[PDB]
Image (cartoon, coloured by chain):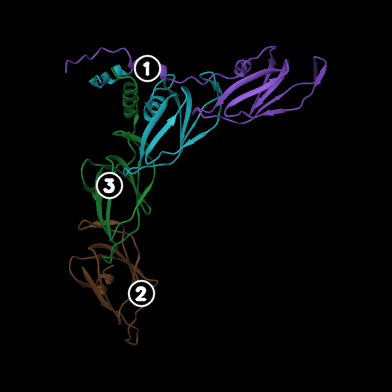
Chain colours: A green, B brown, C cyan, D purple
């Protein structure tokens, strides 16, 4: 995981504790399956901090929705929102790699 | 940016009825400015508030404006009349 | 008989314990009759672990429905899911670019 | 009195104790009348075992109805049903298994 952060305030400078939503498409990364569970994070005194797994994620806040790519090391959430992709990347190559890697783990040399 | 104004009746008494301030979702100085619609009451007819530079939406009761908050302290009427 | 497993998490790397669902069509295995009963399995602290009878099985997880073949020895679930989506039965023996040059890797125990 | 028997599970090897239903058309066996009465049998700890009279019987289970000739001996129930059950729909694991075999072996010296 990587820690992703923002400072969150209203127009009068007071902290705004409304929840941010994080999710992904179903995939394997390291030894683990990542699920489509929508995880809801409160900012605490206006500091938003969340540990995420690298690669594709979905960010939702109010009316807005964004497809972020989480980088390999700690980053500000607004840089990822400003660089968010239009539509999800496919898993077609990854599913072949996983199928081969699975059949190999099922019967080693 | 500090923004201030005195607010009154036609008889020169305080008008402490609430003003409303809001924004689009945006980043300023590395801070996320959320789209929350904040109510502010003048105190003895004085409003004093801190606003982030760039676009802000203002409402009193029926009237509304889209002000552009400058980097320096200013009177709310000069920002309203510029809309 | 045969154990299939996974580690199942959300995009924040915390466990996701929503139910997986397992079933088959009416058929014979090691003498016994296997029925159409939908069996519901919750991961425990993020670990999914299910005894499954070899051969054809159906896996449902939310919107998804995968048709899978349970191997004769213990395995990871995502390899069986990946096999089911990456290799439809009509794959025409395309031979996988030598499994993408085998990713140029292997190791003894 | 012929015992017809089976061991019945779900896909996880756990028992399934949903009832199996046995009946017949009206007919005569060894002089007695056999009626259409539906005999409902529980599998006990996954084991299904029923005494049936020889000749024609109906087996019902969920959506399914099958017709059997109960043989004059002591048969296992899947053998009487099997010709009437659709084969499990062909799925690709054997193809992937072959395609990932055909190695050019690694043999490291360490």
Q: CA distance from mark 1 to mark 2?
A: 72 Å
Instruction: Tell me the residue that label 1 is attached to.
Output: D97
Q: Nearer the viewer, residue A26 or D49?
A: D49
* Quadrant in which residue C94 is drawn: top left
Image coordinates of residue B18 in percent, x first then y, are: 35, 74
A33 is higher (above) or lower (below) than B40 = above
* Quadrant in which residue B5 is drawn: bottom left
Q: CA distance from mark 3 to mark 1?
A: 38 Å
Evaluate whether label 3 is on the same chain as label 2.
no
Local SS, label 1: helix
Image coordinates of residue C5 in percent, x first then y, are: 38, 31
Instruction: Tell me the residue that label 3 is attached to.
Output: A51
B17 is higher (above) or lower (below) than A9 = below
* Quadrant in which residue B80 is drawn: bottom left
Camera-nearest label, 1 or 2? 1
Label 3: few (<14), some or many (≥20) within 10 Å?
Answer: some
């Amino acid at each position: 995981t990587v820690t992703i952060t923002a400072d969150v305030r209203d127009v009068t400078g007071q902290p705004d504790n409304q929840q941010w939503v994080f999710s992904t498409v179903l995939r394997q990364q390291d030894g683990s399956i990542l699920t489509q569970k929508q995880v809801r994070v409160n900012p605490v005194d206006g500091a938003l901090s969340v540990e995420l797994e690298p690669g594709f994620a979905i960010v939702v806040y109010g009316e807005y929705r964004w497809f972020i790519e989480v980088p390999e090391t700690d980053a500000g959430l607004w840089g990822l929102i400003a660089t968010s992709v239009a539509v999800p990347p496919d898993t077609s190559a990854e599913l072949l790699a996983d199928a081969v890697n699975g059949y190999l783990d099922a019967n080693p040399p | 940016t500090t923004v201030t104004a005195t607010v009154h009746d036609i008889s020169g008494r305080p008008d402490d009825s609430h003003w409303t301030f809001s924004s689009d979702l945006r980043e300023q100085d590395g801070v996320i400015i959320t789209p929350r619609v904040v109510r502010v009451k003048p105190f003895n007819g004085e409003l004093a508030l801190t606003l982030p530079p760039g676009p802000v939406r203002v409402t009193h009761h029926q009237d509304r404006w889209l002000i552009d908050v400058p980097e320096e302290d200013s009177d709310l009427w000069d920002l309203i009349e510029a809309a």
